[PDB]
Length: 141
Image (tube, rainbow, N blue to C red):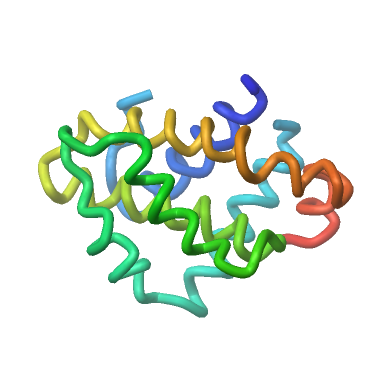
């Protein structure tokens, strides 16, 4: 999905800018504003910044896609719901932040790619069964 690359690239750019980082390294406005709002609400509750999910991953130019997939999957031990998808987006935002902090900016576009693959593969199917991106709009702000 090109519609997905876009969403991923919005949320991360949004998060990177919000927290003072560069978005250079790179979807009705409705879904986009909804994801940004969702992510913000989520992070006020859980300000851990996925501290040990990132420990298990600890991303490097070496890291393979299958590794990110193994670790993101944990968000979904109990399957998909809207909150867990927001967490997915929020977890990538955190991976990007760390990456810039670790002087690994080269990785941020790579993470965006993985997020798209993952969204297309594992999450789109739940999404279409549960109203599509519209219910994120319905649900979030």
